[PDB]
Length: 135
Image (tube, rainbow, N blue to C red; front, side):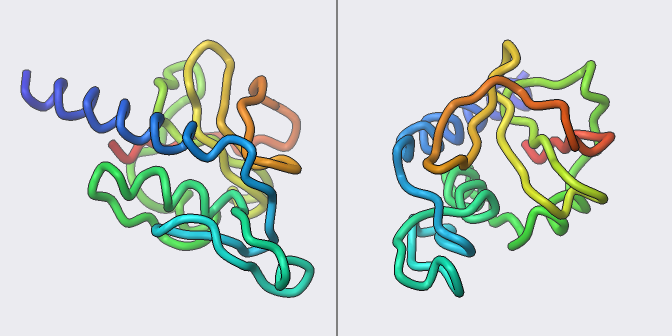
């Protein structure tokens, strides 16, 4: 029972942290565990998040340090069938999840980085075959 409670408690913390960043601008390669930062290249002069950076920030609240890169996140935790998705699960885009990543919020909502950190409907186009549970 404590397992379930800890999972639920962790999930709530991570969602709260992610949601607190709504509106922060996209920055190519920006951000990480400690919050938004300048990125590189096109993002060198912009403080913000890319998808990977935002996930690292949000999940750090549950005492988890996620790998850098969506492609590396796709290779940790438990692979989940999308039909069995729960809030807190990670959704991936591109071949082997290397293009991007977002956090499922339940009811076909996800926290993603668009032009800014935002809550969006789930996008199925280009979605990787599995989701990932780390909590």
